[PDB]
Image (cartoon, rainbow, N blue to C red; front, side, top):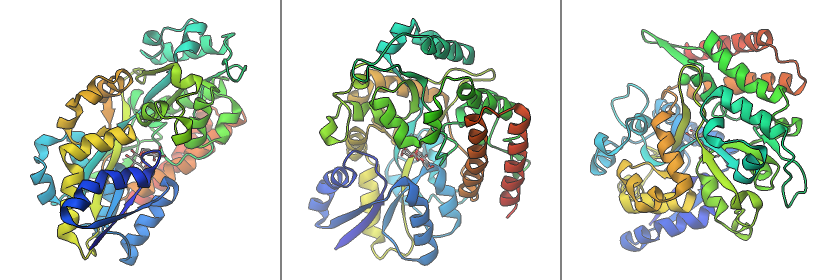
Length: 415
Ligand SMILES: OC[C@H]1O[C@@H](O[C@H]2[C@H](O)[C@@H](O)[C@@H](O)O[C@@H]2CO)[C@H](O)[C@@H](O)[C@@H]1O
Ligand SMILES: [Cl-]
């Protein structure tokens, strides 16, 4: 007997790590778990095709932001039973619990697997040579921009590249998500969507959201981000940070784990950046401090022929032992709140900064139409980045683009 599991590349050897994670389960149940690894870029298509076609695995990893969308298609097995065996609502951060179902659904359709949230990695050697105190740079928007200005005027050169660093790297080219943009929207007092007595609408074109978006996009128009970096997706920006090409960038806690892994095994431990690595939270904006809080859950397709055995695997993957071990293998945080207390997370100095930054963590609402909203937002945000690359992003042009994005988003939400 066999379970099929789909997962995304959460660890450097995603298939091998997952297999090693489920080995005790395989031994004890006398079952094989076959895993297929999907790139995040193809995962949405593969999972929605399994949903519509009725062909796919027993279990899939689902980004937290996708749970609502796939759940609304009516294809997921209820897992209230698994969540009750794992300790129920009390055992989860309420922000994590809200990702176990479509907003306002009767039944849970996803088991929390891991959490991740966003902060700034920074080069400790570069900030020092620029005369930047990270406690000032990462306090406030004004401290953030003043730090980038000292980084731009720095005479520091990476000891391996023999070249200057860019103050900030952020991806322009593949905006697959709003995750990079959301903290800036939120810190201005904005939102991506807003509910008015029931109905959801875009707030991307609200004065507050436009203020946050303009603040962030204009850092790049001011010369703090190289034009190069707007050519690049997330994976290429990570590589540029690892190769010593920039002083600061936003990512999740997986980069700490990759930094202690040799290059031979998919890490960057021998690079200067890994040996001079700091983490600081997103700076507070004029209306508050927020960061993107997400992660992945696991779900069971209602066409599975092995629902009992698959629920046993969900309970195992959701539980204390597998929660600590998978978070170690990935550099993610446990989804299970109790597991955060494991000394191996609490005593990691860079990871403790992610753990404290979770006080300000913020999630998207769990909407049926979420896939559509994110897809439409990034399409329009992509065009704003195109204006940045040409030095032509004005507040008027940004507003014009988010007015169009909001019409597209509202039309999709009315369905
Ligand atoms: O939007 C899909 C989910 O994204 C998750 O973050 C991913 C990101 O998409 C990848 O590009 C790569 O960087 O890995 C990240 C961590 O898995 C996010 O955690 C989820 O909440 C989203 O649903
Ligand atoms: Cl929002």
